[PDB]
């Protein structure tokens, strides 16, 4: 009868994928805007 | 003189001057001021605990032997001895440090009897708390805290039908009839014993290893799982310097340690004794015919058969870090020997978050804390595989892995918000900082590891291939499901570093 706790159990047993991923990219060898 | 230690004649057999012996007293006094010597009451407790675990092993083998229908005489003389290794048997260990134990039983006590019979013997024993006997996923290991003393017990099965109460694992013949998994286990205590016997003065070796191990920990070059040498590796490195200076004190060893090792012409390996061949026909580390052992950057070969390279995980980046940290420590070691610097100046903390311009943020997220610990351990284990793939680009000239990881707990509100936290997007969300499991059996628990980058150097850099391989390499784990766990990698500049990586008072890089 505890609706918040039932939503937690539905969150634990959830079969949906957890997050996703993306490719990374670093910009510039830093000749401009140096430290 | 009349003594020849190591595989080469020493550098100098000269005694310790009054200044060297006085600096040695200052070195030991500094090590004591850091609480690196535990206490006399706690070491006496570890002895009573080990003798208590030895009485259980006899009770353990005797019960399993009677179940195999052994006679009253054979089951009594079956025995079963427990050994120790690692930081404890070397005598170099601080307070709260765990005792790397090892149980030796005859072959009629299988690994199945190790988890089925010994685990209940420990819980019913009124002095064992927090027993986490994990069924073998890597090596038969059991962790608990007998009387508060943390123990890591490793199983080892010998083919000899009886194990006496006074057995020594020095004879190479005992390795026969033993599975390869249980051979590498015994190799842990065989090498720990061989180290303590190949050094001239044992007391000088222990004080020197205390300062070198401490210095390595204070500069994050001690973790083996990321490519830096381990405790046994550092022990063999200070053991080699003790051989070259037989009658020197610990302060002399530490001061000469950094100079000799960073000017050592690698990959000439370090050997505490001539490599001995044995009965079993297995690889014994020959870089002239094995190409795998040839590629070892800084080989440190264990003296016990079979001789293996303990520092095989070292990559190009870790090697450069070790050499550069040895150069800085050497210059400090030279100025403390002239009383121009205190001994405490050598144990300064690292400066990882101020050395590189770009840091590779690697986090591992999970829904529960039990799954988080299992998931955070695997992602860190596959970290050395990422730096090896990052070295192949060589737009990156250096990929420096970091020692530990930062655990933060997010308290998400909606189910759609937790999916963002589980990904690279991090909005203004509450993140509590924790250390380990909670509750004692929508929150998203994370564990972040970093990798420093020094760029070779046009307009942009794409590391999409190593990051994608790292994703599949972590998700290939058999104990994984994308419904609970995930892992992603992000970029971070000097100015973009979080506030957690800086202790109060530090100056963030402003560029």
Image (cartoon, coloured by chain):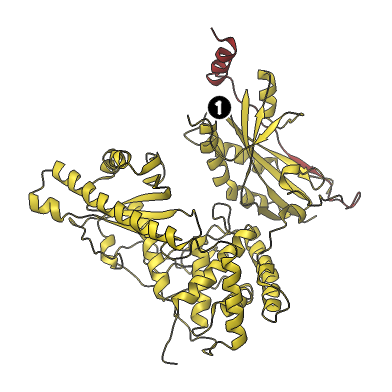
- Residue drawn at x 22%, y 53% is B106
Task: Using the rendered image of the protein, determine whether residue B378 is visible from the camera's viewpoint.
Answer: yes
Q: Position of residue B503 (x, y in %)?
A: 73, 49
Q: Position of residue B98 (x, y in %)?
A: 45, 53
Mark 1 = which residue? B484
| Horizontal side of residue B4 vs B410, given as left or right | left
The answer to which image quadrant residue B48 occupies is bottom left
- Residue drawn at x 9%, y 53% is B73
The relative height of residue B400 versus residue B244 in the rendered view (above or below) is above
The answer to which image quadrant residue B354 occupies is bottom right
**Front one among B30 and B282:** B30
| Horizontal side of residue B38 vs B448, given as left or right | left
The relative height of residue B263 versus residue B439 in the rendered view (above or below) is below
Give the residue furthest to the top: A1
**Front one among B223 and B452:** B223
Q: Position of residue B300 (x, y in %)?
A: 50, 67
Give me the chain letter of mark 1.
B
Label 1 element class: loop
Task: Using the rendered image of the protein, determine whether residue B300 is visible from the camera's viewpoint.
Answer: no
Give the residue furthest to the front: B41
**Front one among B381 and B219:** B219
Give the residue furthest to the bottom: B1
- Residue drawn at x 40%, y 50% is B151
- Residue drawn at x 55%, y 19% is A15
The relative height of residue B203 versus residue A15 in the rendered view (above or below) is below
Chain that the image shows in yellow: B
The relative height of residue B473 versus residue B78 in the rendered view (above or below) is above
Q: Position of residue B356 (x, y in %)?
A: 76, 54
Chain that the image shows in red: A
**Front one among A26 and B379:** B379
Callout 1: few (<14), some (14-19), or many (20+) C-alpha neighbours within 10 Å?
A: many
């Amino acid at each position: 009868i505890s609706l918040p706790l039932l939503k937690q159990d539905d969150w634990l047993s959830s079969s949906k994928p957890f997050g996703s991923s993306t490719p990374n990219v670093v910009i510039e060898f830093d000749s401009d805007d140096d430290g | 003189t009349t003594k020849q230690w190591g595989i080469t004649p020493p550098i100098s057999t000269a005694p310790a001057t009054e200044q060297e012996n006085a600096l040695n007293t200052a070195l030991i006094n500094e090590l004591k001021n850091q609480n690196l010597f535990e206490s006399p009451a706690e070491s006496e407790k570890r002895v009573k605990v080990l003798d208590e675990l030895q009485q259980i092993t006899t009770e353990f083998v005797k019960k399993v032997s009677l179940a195999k229908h052994m006679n009253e005489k054979m089951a009594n003389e079956a025995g079963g001895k427990i050994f120790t290794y690692g930081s404890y048997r070397l005598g170099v260990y601080g307070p709260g440090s765990d005792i790397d134990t090892l149980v030796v039983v005859p072959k009629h006590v299988s690994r199945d009897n190790f988890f089925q019979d010994l685990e209940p013997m420990l819980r019913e024993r009124e002095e064992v708390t927090d027993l986490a006997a994990v069924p073998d996923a890597y090596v038969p290991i059991i962790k608990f805290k007998f009387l508060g003393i943390s123990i890591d017990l490793i199983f080892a099965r010998l083919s000899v039908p009886r194990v006496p109460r006074d057995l020594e694992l020095s004879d190479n013949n005992l390795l026969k009839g033993v599975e390869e998994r249980c051979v590498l286990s015994l190799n842990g205590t065989r090498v720990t014993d061989q180290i303590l016997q190949l050094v001239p003065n044992r007391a000088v070796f222990k004080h020197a290893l205390r300062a070198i191990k401490f210095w390595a920990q204070r500069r994050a070059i001690y973790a083996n799982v990321v490519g830096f040498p381990g405790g046994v590796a550092w022990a063999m490195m200070v053991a080699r310097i003790c051989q070259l200076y037989p009658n020197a004190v610990s302060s002399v060893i530490v001061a000469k340690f950094f100079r000799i090792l960073h000017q050592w012409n690698w990959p000439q390996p370090i050997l505490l004794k001539p490599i001995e061949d044995g009965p079993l026909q297995v690889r014994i580390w020959n870089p002239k015919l094995y190409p795998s052992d040839k590629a070892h950057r800084m080989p440190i070969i264990t003296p016990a058969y079979p001789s293996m390279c303990a520092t095989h995980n070292i990559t190009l980046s870790t090697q450069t870090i070790i050499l550069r940290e040895m150069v800085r420590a050497g210059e400090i070691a030279d100025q403390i020997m002239v009383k121009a610097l205190p001994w405490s100046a050598l144990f300064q903390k690292h400066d990882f978050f101020h050395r590189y311009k770009h840091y590779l943020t690697i986090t591992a997220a999970a829904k529960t804390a039990e799954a988080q610990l299992k998931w955070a351990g695997l992602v860190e284990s596959k970290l050395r595989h990422l730096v090896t793939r990052l070295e192949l680009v060589d737009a990156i000239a250096l990929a420096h892995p970091f020692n530990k990881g930062f655990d933060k707990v997010y308290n998400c509100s909606s189910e759609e918000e937790a999916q963002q936290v589980a990904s690279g997007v991090t909005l203004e969300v509450a993140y509590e900082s924790t250390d380990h499991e909670k509750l004692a059996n929508f929150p998203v628990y994370t564990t972040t590891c970093y990798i420093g980058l020094e760029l070779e150097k046009i307009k942009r850099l794409d590391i999409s291939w190593p990051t994608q391989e790292f994703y599949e390499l972590c998700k290939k784990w058999d104990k994984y499901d994308d419904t609970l766990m995930n892992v992603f990698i992000k970029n971070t500049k000097n100015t973009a570093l979080p506030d957690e990586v800086f202790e109060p008072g530090e100056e963030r890089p402003k560029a």
